[PDB]
Length: 68
Length: 70
Length: 70
Image 1 (cartoon, each protein chain N blue to C red):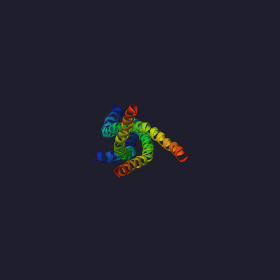
Image 2: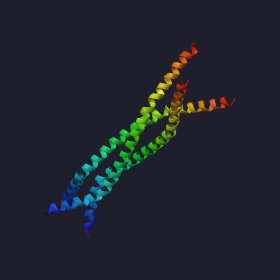
Image 3: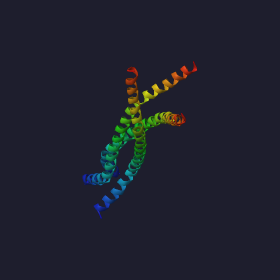
Image 4: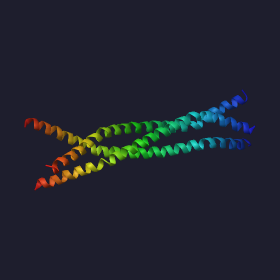
C-alpha cells in the first residue's frame, strides 16, 4: 500500500530522470574531451613559452650591444 | 482514474523538483559549449603557430651545420 | 496527521534517486569551473604572445620590401 506508493514514485521519477541521466552522460564525455584537449594545449604552450622567453632576451642583449 | 490519477499528480509533482535540475543542466550545456568553441579557437591558433616554430628550429639546426664547418 | 509519516517515507525514495544526480552535477560544476579558469589563463598567455608574432611577421614583410629596392 505505502510500498505501492513508493514503487509508483520511484518509477515515475526514474522515467523523468532518463533524459536527465542522458543529458549528464553526454556532458561527462564532452567535459572529458575538453579536459584532454586543454591538457594537450597546455603542454604545447609549455614547450613554446621558453623559446619566446629566449627570443625576448636575445632582443634585450642585442639592444645593449647596439648602444656600445 | 483512481491510482491512475495518483500517478499523474505524482508526475507533475516530480516535474516541479526537476525544473531546478533542468535549469542547472541547461546553464552547464551552454557554458560547456562556450568553452568547447573557445578551446576550438585556441587549438587552431596553436596548430597555425606550431609549424613555423618547427621550421624555425630546423633553420637554427641547418645554420649550425653550415657555420662550424666553413 | 499521518500524512507526515507518508511524506517522510516517499521523500526517502526521491532522495535516494536524486542524491547521485546532485553529486554528478556538483562534480561537473567544479570541473567545469576548473577548465574555465585554465582556459582564461591560456587565452591571456596567447593574448600576450599573438602581438610579438604579428610584430615579427611585419618585420619580415618590411625587410622583403627593402630587399626589392636593393
